[PDB]
Image: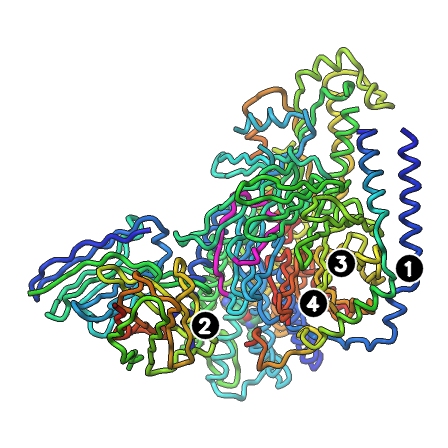
Amino acid sequence: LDQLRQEAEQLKNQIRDARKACADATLSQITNNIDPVGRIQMRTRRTLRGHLAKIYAMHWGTDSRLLVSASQDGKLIIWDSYTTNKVHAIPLRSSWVMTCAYAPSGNYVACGGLDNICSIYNLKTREGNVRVSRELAGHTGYLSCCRFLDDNQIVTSSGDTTCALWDIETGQQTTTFTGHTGDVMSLSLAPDTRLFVSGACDASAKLWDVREGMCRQTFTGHESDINAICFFPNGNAFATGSDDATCRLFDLRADQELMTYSHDNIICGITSVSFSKSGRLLLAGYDDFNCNVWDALKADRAGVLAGHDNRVSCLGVTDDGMAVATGSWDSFLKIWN
Amino acid sequence: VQLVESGGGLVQPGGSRKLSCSASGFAFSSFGMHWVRQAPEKGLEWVAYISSGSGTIYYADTVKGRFTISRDDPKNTLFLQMTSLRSEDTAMYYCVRSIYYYGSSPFDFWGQGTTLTVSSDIVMTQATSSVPVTPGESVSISCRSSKSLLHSNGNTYLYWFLQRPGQSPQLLIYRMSNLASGVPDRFSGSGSGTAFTLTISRLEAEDVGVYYCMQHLEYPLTFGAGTKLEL
Amino acid sequence: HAYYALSYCALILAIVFGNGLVCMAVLKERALQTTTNYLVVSLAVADLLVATLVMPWVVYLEVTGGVWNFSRICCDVFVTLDVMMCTASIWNLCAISIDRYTAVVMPVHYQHGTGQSSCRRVALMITAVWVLAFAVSCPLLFGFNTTGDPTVCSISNPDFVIYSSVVSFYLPFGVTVLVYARIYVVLKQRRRKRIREKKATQMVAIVLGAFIVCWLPFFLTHVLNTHCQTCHVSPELYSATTWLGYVNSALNPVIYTTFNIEFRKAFLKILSC
Amino acid sequence: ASIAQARKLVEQLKMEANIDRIKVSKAAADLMAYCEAHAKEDPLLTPVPASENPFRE
Amino acid sequence: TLSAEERAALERSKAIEKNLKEDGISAAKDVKLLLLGAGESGKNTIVKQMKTTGIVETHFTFKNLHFRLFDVGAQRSERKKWIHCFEDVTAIIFCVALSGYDQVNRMHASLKLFDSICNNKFFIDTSIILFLNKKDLFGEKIKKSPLTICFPEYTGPNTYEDAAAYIQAQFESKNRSPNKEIYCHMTCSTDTNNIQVVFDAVTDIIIANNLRGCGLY
Ligand SMILES: C[C@H]1CO[C@@H](c2ccc(N)nc2)CN1C[C@H]1C[C@@H]1CCNC(=O)c1cc2ccccc2[nH]1
């Protein structure tokens, strides 16, 4: 029916016009007066060795000390970052994991990958071993990202162009967040854990309401597939990273691309993005073997975290914002501070 | 999870005895095992420790050479071969599991124990002994250490244990703050380096028993005298 | 005659530069840290110690007119170190030949020059080479190099000379040649069974041609001199043979590393400034 | 789905249109306010002294 | 220095390190293969000869070599998002059905897929074990239908040997990296000897890699 197509066209036009109407000025113009942060020299405090394959994901614990790491050797290594002690080494049923999550409480760890199953491992067992607490099956594509709402419910994103809110106890999809045209690659929980943003391969980041279970806003602007996404600390903005070698800060309330972070010397894709505690620094992991720390308000390349011998796959910032942990394909986890 | 130990009996002073504790219901291979004895009508006294993998073995100064501890992972068994005995070696020997990682709760589970009879360090003191309480009000048990337990890393290695009358000691608190799994929130441990306090907000019928304060800063592990709370 | 002194100094500078570059390349880069590379590092070390601990005494002998003025122990340590270094280099060449033979004929356990089997095999080879060079070289330090006029420093004991020449050069040369010949025939047989040969063949031809051209004419003339009725071994011939003996030490880095793509990109990264 | 998918996406764009968008300058001011208010307790902006740095030798 | 608990935790970490080491040494000897076919290209036949969702693991030992074959059928999404997962695969067992040239076109899609995989930036130093399955059906299909229907400007006889040789040559094209060696082999239904040719190809790839590391290739 052409009436629906033309009506959707006029709708898109109305959305674009509404977005443009409220865009009176740019963040770059407003932030020209503020003093620019001086260059930051973060040193490699620790190097976590032990993985024997490409590290694909990591997730800091809420105590900012423990961190879990997932690689292609079928191992979930939970490290003690302070002492570089391997706290746990969980052997994976499928050695094809692309994500790993640490529960806020610090009791469970979730991972998954090309097996299309979100394996949840209980750490606080009376037997003193880590056993598979739950096997969340149902996604028809590879599991790209997973984040715990709490110990009972977990949101995951899959390569079948779908996010799913699961209830761990029952092991069924409580909610199904559909709408992305391309494979959903990243997730980012809002601080209040009410809404979440998901960046897919259709060059669009979609905001979903966890309770209602349906999309709220859609943000476009990237010229390629989005790989990473991360909320701003306050929970009103979020930054994305794509294969077009650009970071994009969008604002939820303004509902439009707020600012871009691109350099003419950078051409490789982006794999991970994270904010500092205050949100002033935007740390992005690139495929040029090093991480770049940008000024979130000036788009000035504050620093370059170099040292990894392969593509930077994942990075995370602690809850207290003390150090940043970068996991790369060279099978190394470097902690920078 | 259970530890069933056997071997306890009447032994001539010069005789040898082989205590065998069979563990079942948990990953025995990955737990550090302690032989801790309680002399008749006396407090706890740590005897020996063997680490996960039989890599590290420690003995108390009073049993060095005489006693030997050995582990059998295939069959999940712990052995205590005591060669030479004395009149002071009669005790109730408990097998205590203790896994050691960051955030772990070592000494969480205790075995039933075997009553065997026969025919410098951190001086842990309490100076409390008997405390006569009626159920309902708060109770404050004070433990004192000869050496400051606050390690530079930033935690104190104090362990509150509850031995109910005629039962195996149970872990109440580890690192003087963290309550053990299954312990109600009434128990609250506090302290500073030397002086430590265990507070029970509301005492019930089941709280009657002996309260031991153990140090875990460095071997040998020394227990307190034991504060007995009763009606 | 000063031409020799300056040319030997230039050789020393070339050797130390080449080996320092190979060592730092292998050290900083992590893709080069392979068991097969440890043999190349061993060879680089050997040639660096040739340039440092041995060569300046050859320069001294040259500039002084070939007369020894130091103590007899300094001549004994000179001939000892010299022989030890040269034998180590030659047997390192043989060790790399055996390593590539294992790589070809025994591929499953070789894997990619990694693991316990490969690491222990390389460690064993290196050890066996260094201890063999020691066994060969230590006689002279024990006052075995019998000499006449005490103002000359040379190896002139045919009982030592013939056996050292046989064990130190002739045996590893025969082994290297046989091994590379077997690698060649095995590769050609596999290529025929199937139904870059040019690269492998060229590398084997160049490595064996550089080893022969630089080491054979010394040992040959040395053994003819020590055992012959009357052979006119002119001083300038001996000097040319020693020269070739040390240009092998200079050339080896180039022939072994500069032709490796990962080494090429490494050196180009180091010399980007 | 032809008709079903077209109706779904049109309804999604309809509910997306009914969103109260604040001014971009206001959003930017809130980003400033937050960045600066928490600048003091962000140990990545400034080198934390070794006394209270948990990642050291 | 370290407290009793810190020391026991360090010992635990060392035991974990030792286990990770042993597991790595045990797993490093495995030959990892990626069965990358196209629908009904003869993946089920070849895997049945060698031996609900997600990739399929087929592990089999043959003459002191443990081959772990990975079949990616359930992944209907875009390839590139998980191709990097199999970056260090020893070889790609690409299966193509010879019969599917006139009937659908199928063959053009197979050539396009082969082009995409072979020229992928992750598969640069990766050999392809090309299998031309269902040769029996092509035997009579070529005698009935000419090959020109699928490949214009063939300009050759529609015989048995040359038609397959041409198809093979057209598949050996679209190969740029000299390091890549396509081991084309024509199979038919079930022969019970495709494991032998797989072994021979794998060992040839291993030798090639060893000589490339030593610097002879
Ligand atoms: C060639 C290597 C190879 O390594 C040694 C070797 C290794 C193994 C083996 N079996 N045998 C020998 C044998 N070297 C021989 C080299 C150390 C001597 C130096 C010879 N210059 C003189 O003496 C000299 C200079 C001069 C100038 C003017 C007049 C008289 C003069 N005389």
- Do the residues at discs 3 and 1 belong to one chain? yes
Query: The disc labelled 1 sits on which kind of residue?
Result: Ala
Question: x and y percent of residue A265 in the render?
Answer: 82, 63
Residue for point 78% across, 33% down: E112
Q: Is residue B121 left or right of residue A141?
A: left
Q: Residue B147: percent from the left, percent from the top? A: 35, 82
Mark 4, residue position: A276
The colour scheme is rainbow
Image height of C226 relative to B121, above or below:
above
- For the residues labelled 4 and 2, the Cα–Cα distance comes to 76 Å
- Mark 3 vs mark 1, foreground winner is 1
Q: Residues within 10 Å of mark 2 (few under 14, many from 20)?
A: some
Marks 1/4: CA–CA distance: 27 Å
Q: Secondary structure at mark 3?
A: strand
Answer with the quarter of the image where residue D41 lies: bottom right
Which residue is found at the position 13% from the left and 67% from the top?
Answer: B84
Q: Give the quarter of the image for residue C268.
A: bottom right
**Which residue is nearer to you in this view: D26 or E43?**
D26
Q: Which residues are magenta?
A: A85-106
Q: Is residue A234 visible in the rendered structure shown here?
A: yes
SS of the residue under disc 4: loop
On residue A23, the disc is 1
B80 relative to A60 in the view: left or right? left
The kind of residue on which mark 4 rests is Ser
Which residue has dot 3 on it? A238
Q: Position of residue C225 (x, y in %)?
A: 53, 68
Indicate which label's residue lies in the foreground, 1 or 4.
Answer: 1
Q: Pointer 1 and pointer 4: residues touching (CB < 8 Å)?
A: no
Q: Quadrant of ligand 1?
A: bottom right
